[PDB]
Image: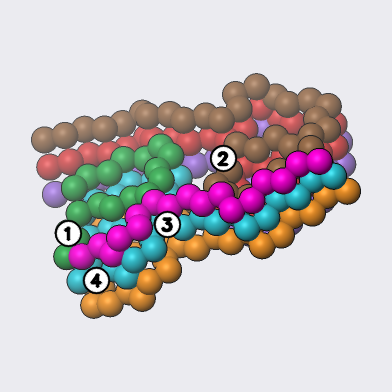
Chain colours: A cyan, B orange, C green, D purple, E red, F brown
């Protein structure tokens, strides 16, 4: 008998403002210029 | 007997404002210019 | 009998402001220029 | 002056045979039973 | 002047055979039973 | 003047056979039972 619950995963937990660049949460491969 | 529940995954948990760039949550391959 | 719960994983727990570069949370492979 | 080219991303580069389960390349959310 | 090229990212570079379980390349969130 | 090229990232470079469990390459969050 097992029980897994209430795990929680966040990437940004605060409002982003006035961005002008490249804000990515998860990136597999690929290039970013900024 | 198993039981998995109430897992939770967020990428942005705060309102975004005045953006001018590239805000991506998950990106597989691909280029980004900003 | 096991019980795993309430684990929590954050990448940014504070609002980002006035960004102009490359803010990435998790990056597998891939290049970044900034 | 920038130049990005010839990036390449593969998920399975070899022929699959005699499958009987769940072969997924990329999965966001969602459950899999097999 | 920059130049990024010929990056390469693979997940499985060998043919899979006689599978009976759950073969996933990339999985964000979500449960897997096997 | 910069030059980045020919980077290479593999997860499985050998054919998988007779699997019966959960073979994942990259997993963000989420549970696995096997």
Q: Chain of mark 3?
A: A
- Residue D12 in view of the camera: no
Instruction: Tell me how far mark 1 sits from mark 3, CA to CA.
Output: 19 Å
The mark lying in front, picked from 3 and 2, is 3
The rendered magenta stretch, by its main secondary structure, is classed as loop
Mark 4 highlights which residue? A17
Which stretch is magenta? C1-17
The mark lying in front, picked from 2 and 4, is 4
Question: For numbered disc 1, what is the local secondary structure?
Answer: loop
Residue E23, how many percent across, how many down? 72, 40
Which residue corresponds to the image point at 61% horizontal and 27% vertical from the top-left?
F12
- Mark 1 burial class by Cα count in 10 Å: few <14, some 14-19, many 20+: some
Mark 3 highlights which residue? A11
The mark lying in front, picked from 1 and 3, is 3
- Mark 3 burial class by Cα count in 10 Å: few <14, some 14-19, many 20+: many
Q: Quadrant of residue A7?
A: bottom right
- Mark 2 burial class by Cα count in 10 Å: few <14, some 14-19, many 20+: some
Image quadrant for the C terminus of chain B?
A: bottom left
Asked if labels 1 and 2 share a chain, the reply is no
Q: Chain of mark 1?
A: C
Question: For numbered disc 4, what is the local secondary structure?
Answer: loop
- Along the line of sight, the residue nearer the viewer: B25 or A29: B25
Which residue corresponds to the image point at 46% horizontal and 30% vertical from the top-left?
F9
Instruction: Tell me how far mark 3 sits from mark 2, CA to CA.
Output: 17 Å
Q: Quadrant of residue D7?
A: top left
């Amino acid at each position: 008998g097992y029980e897994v619950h209430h795990q929680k995963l966040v990437f940004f937990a605060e409002d982003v403002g006035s961005n002008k660049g490249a804000i990515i949460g998860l990136m597999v491969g690929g290039v970013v210029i900024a």
